[PDB]
Amino acid sequence: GSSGSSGEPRRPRAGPEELGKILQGVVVVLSGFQNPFRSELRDKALELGAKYRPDWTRDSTHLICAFANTPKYSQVLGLGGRIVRKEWVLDCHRMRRRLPSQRYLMAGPGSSSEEDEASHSGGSGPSSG
Figure 1 (spheres, helix red, strand yellow):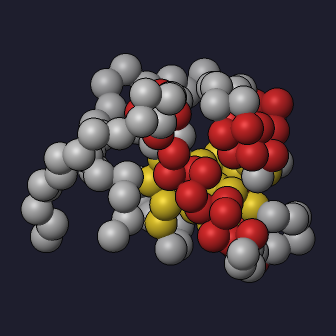
Figure 2 (figure 1 turned 180 degrees about the vertical axis):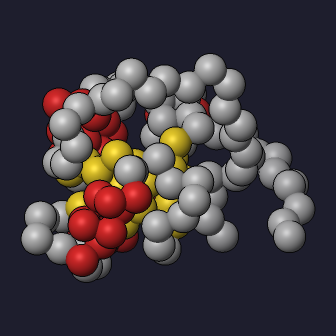
């Protein structure tokens, strides 16, 4: 468990608040990444407001792959998860905007009109102590 306690004046600039509203309710998984790149990539993903899991979870909506022909690629492929490239996160953070993952689709015939109506969120502390 983790308690929620935070209080401090932040800069006026558009902090992680605006970005957190981009991927609000999304879960990204890092696969085939090595620091410092691995670290940099993760952070960015957090800003957008996406959840970073150490492995494919039942709550995982999108998978961040560094290159095809990987073990974690086919795995999430057969399951039915949305396998996309990193360019999605890099561009999202870099542009701090919501980009269509469909254009960055690695596997699958295409979005099967699978949209969400009501999702849950949490983690009122993007500051990974």
